[PDB]
Image (cartoon, rainbow, N blue to C red; front, side, top):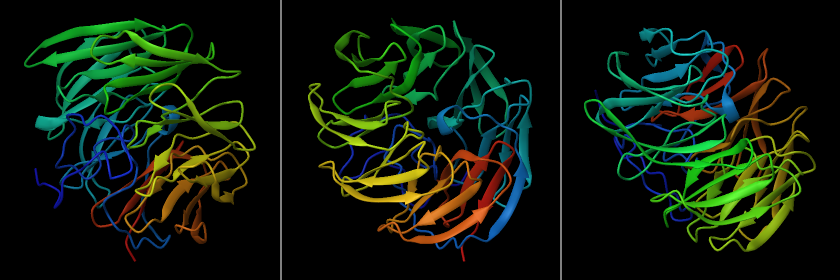
Length: 373
């Protein structure tokens, strides 16, 4: 289909994700393993453009992807993957793809969607048509989105306590590059840094730095409680990870503690990082935090329930997020409220921006679209 007018980049000057084989022509091909600072501006003012019924239980704030045409792809817990036109009408639908929990339909190159399924499978789906190209079995249910490496390898965690590195070779060879048995249930989903390290962590309180070429552990640390969600990585290779003990931890690429930052409650979302190195995270306290690269609070913004959406930053520094108080929120770069929108289900499916500034965000029951002013 069409291409976005500028290429998608996982990184800006202040982030340090491993560049992988994502659809560079897409508007938003991945939810995580990128800065979550959009290259697009938005004038969205809080007026709803449309809503669709999309029943879901997204893992760690998973949600929609958007290709170069602006087609919106989202999985629902009734077994469907649906492609929506920008006007909210349906372009295609494929059924029987997995229930109970949903994940992001990540867009790779050559128009392939990578969708792990609760049926213990990894689907490869044609984004133009919805056709299932083929699928690979997994030994346990997947507990992460598919991260894509520079050679096309897919990295996922599974519920039977593994990190998998799966290399697909067209038209139908799927190869275990390596598999790592973790000590405990994976709570921190795999993200990859520019130096080749994959980071993950378990509820036996172990945080791992793994060589993504070999699957061998580089170093590990234990903590009092478990990390959860998707960390962000800065340009120096420092990893910022939210912990259930109520702190954000910053670990350097060598495993040194750069700092910790208190969140007043369990970490409740995954992170974003802006091009000035500020990092953003939600808390079970109800607050969204903006924190500097040196660990100082820039601001906090209170909501009436846990903030479980990973925040999204636009090109002007505005921050979009949602809360278990059932509001979508937009604030400016200094934390000033711009608008809120009251819906009827907790806002937990993380926001996505299209090229024209349309903002998509989801609840347990709905996909919401907020148009430009």
